[PDB]
Amino acid sequence: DPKPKFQEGERVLCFHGPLLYEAKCVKVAIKDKQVKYFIHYSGWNKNWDEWVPESRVLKYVDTNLQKQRELQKANQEQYAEGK
């Protein structure tokens, strides 16, 4: 569907599990009105590179970095509780 949120090359934050990671938008493909993104997670081996729907990609900005940090601590709180 005309004009997607992200561009090839764009540094981004991408959701993977319950966590957000820095990442790059390697590819942008449109399918059936649904825009998809092929992503390489930075500092991550290319095998984990994957296709992701738009809803999993967030702009690399202060608001989302703060969200990243809050999910990190929340997750870290889950790990710490798992013992």
Image: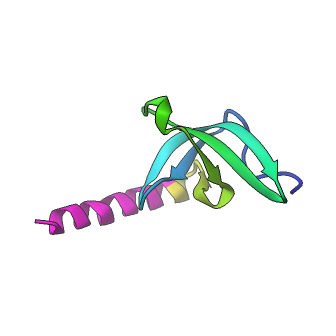
Left or right: 66, with 9 as reference point: left
For this rendering, which residue is in front, 6 or 27?
Answer: 27
Instruction: Check residue 82 for magenta coloring.
Output: yes
Answer above or below: position of 23 versus 14.
above
- Report the residue that reaches farthest toward the right: 2
**Image location of residue 65, percent across then percent down:** 48, 53
Report which quarter residue 19 is drawn in.
bottom left
The answer to whether residue 75 is magenta is yes
The magenta region covers 65-83
Instruction: Name the dominant secondary structure of the magenta segment.
Output: helix
On the image, the x and y values in percent for residue 71 come to 39, 62
Is 58 left or right of 36, judged from the image as shown?
left
70 displayed left or right of 64: left
Q: Residue at x 89, y 54 (%)?
A: 2
Residue 52, image x and y in percent? Answer: 62, 51
- Taking the spot 24% from the left edge, 66% from the top edge, the residue there is 77
Q: Residue at x 86, y 57 (%)?
A: 1
Q: Residue at x 53, y 57 (%)?
A: 64
Q: For this rendering, which residue is in front, 32 or 43?
A: 32
Q: x%, y% of residue 34?
A: 78, 59
| Count of labels in the image | 0
- Above or below, comparing residue 12 to residue 58 in the picture: above
